[PDB]
Amino acid sequence: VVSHF
Amino acid sequence: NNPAIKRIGNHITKSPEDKREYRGLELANGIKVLLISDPTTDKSSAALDVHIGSLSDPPNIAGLSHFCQHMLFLGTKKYPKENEYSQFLSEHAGSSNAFTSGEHTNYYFDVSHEHLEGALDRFAQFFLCPLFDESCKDREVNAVDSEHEKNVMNDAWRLFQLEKATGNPKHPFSKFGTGNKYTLETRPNQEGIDVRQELLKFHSAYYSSNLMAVCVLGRESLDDLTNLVVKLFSEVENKNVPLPEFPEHPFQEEHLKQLYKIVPIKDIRNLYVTFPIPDLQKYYKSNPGHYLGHLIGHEGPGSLLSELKSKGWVNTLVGGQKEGARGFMFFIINVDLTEEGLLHVEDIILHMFQYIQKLRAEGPQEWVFQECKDLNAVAFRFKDKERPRGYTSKIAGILHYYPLEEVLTAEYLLEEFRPDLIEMVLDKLRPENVRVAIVSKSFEGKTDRTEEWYGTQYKQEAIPDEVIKKWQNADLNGKFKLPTKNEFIPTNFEILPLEKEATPYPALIKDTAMSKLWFKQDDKFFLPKACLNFEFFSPFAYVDPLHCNMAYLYLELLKDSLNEYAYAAELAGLSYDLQNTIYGMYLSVKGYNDKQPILLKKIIEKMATFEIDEKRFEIIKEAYMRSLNNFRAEQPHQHAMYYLRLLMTEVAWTKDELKEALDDVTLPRLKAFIPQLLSRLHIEALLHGNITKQAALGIMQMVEDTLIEHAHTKPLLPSQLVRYREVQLPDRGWFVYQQRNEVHNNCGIEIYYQTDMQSTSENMFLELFCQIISEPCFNTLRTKEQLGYIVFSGPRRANGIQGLRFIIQSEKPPHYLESRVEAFLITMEKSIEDMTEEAFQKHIQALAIRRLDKPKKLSAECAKYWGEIISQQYNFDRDNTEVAYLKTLTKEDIIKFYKEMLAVDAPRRHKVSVHVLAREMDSCPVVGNLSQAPALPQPEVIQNMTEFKRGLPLFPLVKPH
Ligand SMILES: [Zn+2]
């Protein structure tokens, strides 16, 4: 997953 | 023309689907402002974000700006009463919170739409003339101490702080933001500091209008909102404070190529890989770090994670950019570790570097950028209408970063392809710039450093030049491929016309042995989205601890095998939730309706034809055993809640029964359970959104047909549609269950005053009483008595039954917490006797507004319907009906309800208490300025949950509407 949130 | 306004922005760019109207402006004193007019809204809202936080604390008073955040709520010159602000919000259907980060202090509220000015007038004074009263300063420091105490044994907070402790100790980044009683009272007293003056100095120094941004959302016209904000905020004084800036990275040369070995509280195993980077915030139109985060954090075929998971080294991966402050950021790649992965950390990191090398070799891909941009443009156009309170808070923070005209779009719309920035950031992701942290219980006794705020045990080591050199020579690995075109990207956004037979509530459009289908075509939001919710009933999901484990494991294994294929859908705005329940399984599919039947068909088909990979089985079984064990490290109040559920529900397997049955879960046994689970089902569904009756009937029948085809599924009997009951407590009884939390050195308590089965009258008696005592008992049990940071009261609803609960976490023993709650309740009877009828009617009105508040987006409306469906009450019009009844109630009615069900000598009092003792309260007694606590009876102490349950009746279940 992309670092977020 | 208007001296108080420096400028009005041009048109604020919004989604064409957004009916709210917007005006940006800057006041003469420098405050950046967004006004949001929504003539439909039920709750109005405002937020103010000051561009100062923790990183600006004095080095000698750690946590000051966070303490100051607490203090602002506790009275101002215009409105000196300590809870005037919170009382007024509570009496007008509002709520408020605030937070402090390294660079921002953000304060926000919502309120009934007719009381915006009243709420905002009080709020505005926080920024003008706080009192910082000496007596509430002395009390409120305990709340902040108690906020820190709950975080101490939390792995994420310990790691957040350990990072800061291992960078340059001279950088503001190393500061402890939270503060505690030591940093905020004890040490300042020792050092002769007057904390009241320090709060006043810090507020005076940094609460300057030039660092503030304000957002207001109301029913009022944009001109009326404009006059309001001018009226209230143009008196904030401009001290022209320079914006703090941190151009020097906290991680300098000597902090790079370092390895940390850290002992966690929970039995967890993780690897954290960090590279310092420049601040990329100014590049938001191209966003090079997001582009790289998308690629490196990808989970589809060809990805970094696919290879690490195939090797059996890792199960999940996060990557991409991470905020630091104005002047610095981080780029991370974090993974959890299997037991094998733990022994292969060097290889994991080499694979990371080979994947990064692959990105260098292929070069920046405009088609990837273009996909990101296309997805962001669709997400922006069709974004769900936000709740006002979170919306104003979020826009207040970002008004500091973007031109007025761009505040709504700036975070979504990508404009510029920047292969030069992408290479530049990629050039930072090199082994010479790396920090590596490994978290594992294996390091216990092998560490020689202690972080001072949390007690974290760790060891630091230079990474050997040999290891670095090997990472530097990472070449291409044939396993790593860029993703291909995302085919889940939606292209059909047509809004089907409203059918002639469309209903305001879901309609039962199918009622068969196999399935019950509730359906509503969206008549409100008109976005191309739908929610497809399915409850699968099967008595085999919970028949015993072993089956319950197997249900869980089956669904985790399914989600794990689907993950590569579902990740594309999830980037494309189509997600799903799949979990085992005490009744069977729950499935939800949400997002763009376009490709949604495809993902759904794939899930059912995979479920019904599932083949377990034995290696994935063993890894996920080991994670699940640790997950069951790790509950011991949850918070005392979470323990109190968990035990009450176990006590009050007819059937409930404990974590210990689950973990003991887990050794008996074998592959052969799981393989046999699955066809058994699926052999007989009942399906209750809600299909709600941009969909027709016939598409709904078709999706429903497709799901049944797939289960019938591959799993030979047959319907359940109506009589096997078994709901569990709540234990029925005896008139005048008081039972106590006691346990110890072996990790945290606080107590938790949950007190439950069970009333009776849910119905129109019982619901609203309870909810009104709650409304009335809600702010007072926060005010009493926290603000005045400072029993803890976590102080909760409100209805408890389970299994068709209800009652009043209190949840507190504290350093004080549970028997003590109990006397204080009992003292509180007497205060509330006197207070209800003493309150005017108009004060009484404002509470009815506040509860009314809360209950009638309209969903702003599809999924909030679905959730309401779904609560009716899964409770089997099917009361879709409950809100109008309950509210009409509520307005009938009198002061006399609530006094009588209290006296009959709630008072200490109430004839129908049914009290159960869960006492969770702090790590260090050894054993302990169950019984034992300040208002006077009544004498309590001797409780019956619960020794055995099974016996307790056997010895009591069970309630009926609520009848369906
Ligand atoms: Zn706080």
Image: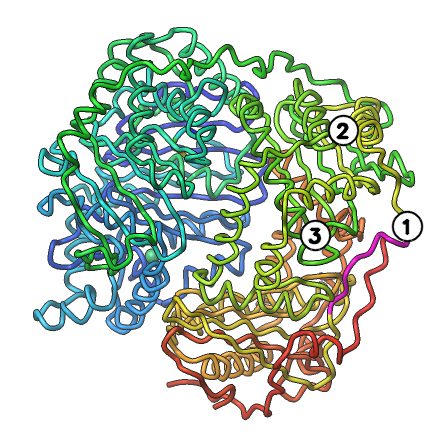
Q: What amino acid type should be assigned to the residue bearing mark 2?
A: Gln
Number of marks drawn: 3
Residue A5 showing in the rendered view: no
Using the image as rendered, state which of residue B857 and residue B737 is in the foreground. B737
Using the image as rendered, state which of residue B112 and residue B614 is in the foreground. B614
SS for dot 2? strand
**Residue B784 belongs to magenta span:** no
Q: What amino acid type should be assigned to the residue bearing mark 1?
A: Pro
Residue B458 showing in the rendered view: yes
Residue pictured at 65% horizontal, 62% vertical: B653
10 Å crowding of disc 2: few (<14), some (14-19), many (20+): many
Residue pictured at 41% horizontal, 27% vertical: B23
Residue B867 at x, y percent in the picture: 71, 48
Name the residue tied to disc 2: B521
> What's the chain of the residue with tag 3?
B
Give the CA distance from mark 2 to mark 3. 37 Å
Work out which quarter of the rendered image holds the N terminus of chain B and state it: top left
Residue B163 at x, y percent in the picture: 23, 45
Q: Earlier in the sequence, mark 2 or mark 3?
A: 2
Q: Point out the stretch of residues depicted in magenta.
A: B719-726
Residue B573 at x, y percent in the picture: 56, 24
Name the residue tied to disc 1: B718
Q: What amino acid type should be assigned to the residue bearing mark 3?
A: His
Give the CA distance from mark 1 to mark 2. 28 Å
Q: Earlier in the sequence, mark 1 or mark 2?
A: 2
Which labelled disc corresponds to residue B547?
3
Q: Is residue B546 left or right of residue B62?
A: right
10 Å crowding of disc 3: few (<14), some (14-19), many (20+): many
**Residue B721 belongs to magenta span:** yes
Ligand 1's quadrant is: bottom left
Residue pictured at 46% horizontal, 67% vertical: B636
In front: mark 3 or mark 1?
3
